[PDB]
Amino acid sequence: AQYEDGKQYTTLEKPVAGAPQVLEFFSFFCPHCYQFEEVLHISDNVKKKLPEGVKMTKYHVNFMGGDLGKDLTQAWAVAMALGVEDKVTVPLFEGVQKTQTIRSASDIRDVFINAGIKGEEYDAAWNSFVVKSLVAQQEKAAADVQLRGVPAMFVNGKYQLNPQGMDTSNMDVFVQQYADTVKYLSEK
Image (cartoon, rainbow, N blue to C red; front, side, top):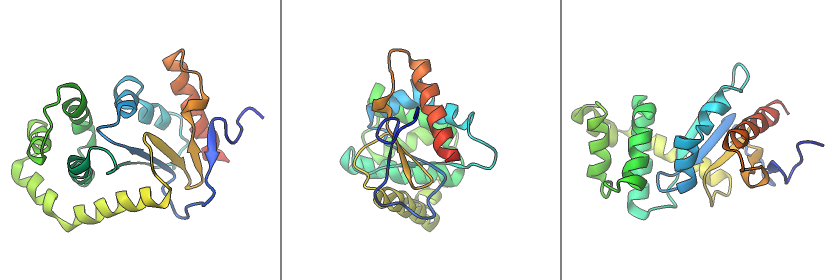
């Protein structure tokens, strides 16, 4: 066929029931993640090709960048709870990987303050049990699926994107292939 298991995707040996329809994992320490977000806009171009009714989930992971890696997972939980993902994703990536001004929880916080979320609002969110459960979810979802590397996308808890099996000579072509694949997997 044109899409083959082991080529553009792999199948999970141990399918994850009740998983989000399109589930994506990343880390602000992850260099391909930076690429995926700021150069390629993967999440975005996938959405543009998903059918009606399909929700997209994105989670941060702990296994990169030690202590600040966990801090980043909690802050992403804050971002999700407050609905400010789109206002912090870029300053977080650049603060971790470009300018390297993110070294502590306090620097993560500064990014939110600069993005216009209020101090009190952030600290309350930061400490809330709603953020605790949201952290728990991020970890649970990663745990369910063997997760040892990012970026990673899983469709219907069953299939995992395999970008190493796609051409990278042209970036636009890589994105569309990636996106079309998710759509195919989506419909399967």
